[PDB]
Every structure is written in C-alpha cells, then in structure tokens.
Length: 164
Image (cartoon, rainbow, N blue to C red; front, side, top):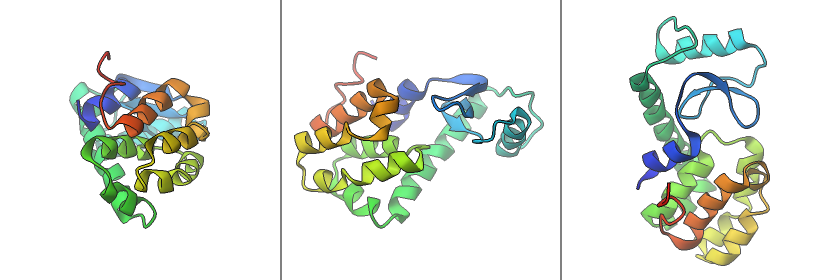
C-alpha cells in the first residue's frame, strides 16, 4: 500500500466526466474539473488539463498522468503551508499518506476542520486526534472515506485499506 493505491481506492477511476460527492464535475481518479454547474465549463477545463480537444472522455494513461500531478500538487500544498508543513514533517510515512489524502482536492471547509486537529497529530495523541477528526466536515460527508483516513492517522498502519 502507498498514497497512490490508497487514493485509487478512495476515489475510484472513471474515464468519462462524472460528478463527485459534492456534485462537482470531475474525471479520472478524483480530478476535480470545476465547481461550475456548466458541463461546457467542465469540458473546457478537461481539454486544458489534458492538452487536447477531448469528448469528455480520457484514456487510463491520461487519468493516471493527471493523478500523479494531483498527488504532487497535494504534497506541494502541504510543504508550502505554514500550518501543514510542521505537522507533515512530524509524521511517519504512513500517516503522511493520510495527510496527503485529507489535502487531496479537499474543500476549504474540509481543510479548515482538519487544521483544528493538527495540534493533536503533532503531539502524537492519536486517539484524541481521531476523535477530533470525526467532527470534521469531511467525516459528515463521507463517513466511510473519513473512517479509513482517521484509522490510518490513529494506527499508523494500512489496516483500513488491506481488505480493499
């Protein structure tokens, strides 16, 4: 298991434009295109992302290319953020993966709520952090996806992803 396999489990893979859990146009492995309700606007973003005039449809190779870019962007975002970087630096590699997921194409509200749990993570108060995390908006929206990520933070193991 690793961050790529982890997010592949949590996001799935779809090669045609679809709507994510918030109703936003998305493609591939959870690549958010736009928050606009316009499918045309979504298609425009897709073409710009891929570098060709698509039919709202991409290949698996293209989906994986975007995915790698998005994983990179998440790590980049963490390392450039004054609140996230020290917590990330403080974590083991398994828990770092959980952070990458929480940061991966996450809403501003999700990030806001996650920030509140950062103190617990950095102190390595795992059970307390887990409880505090369950209060987050991410958990309310997708209790299952949040439960896996929280279990990863709580245990520092891949146990929540091993049956998957």
